Image 1 (tube, rainbow, N blue to C red):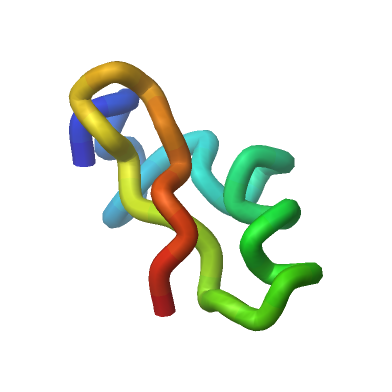
Image 2: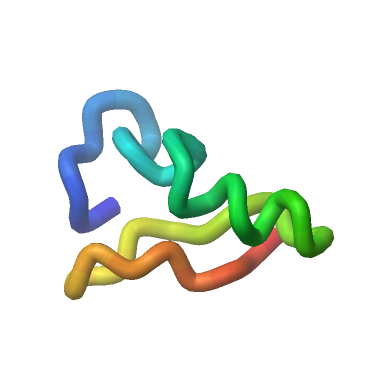
Length: 40
């Protein structure tokens, strides 16, 4: 969870993953380059 790893993956759902959630995916894991790649 390259981003913070406070609890599985800090940030993530915060807003970045929210975009993927609206799409249909669970969210997006913490990419090394701080990118929330849409994934379930």
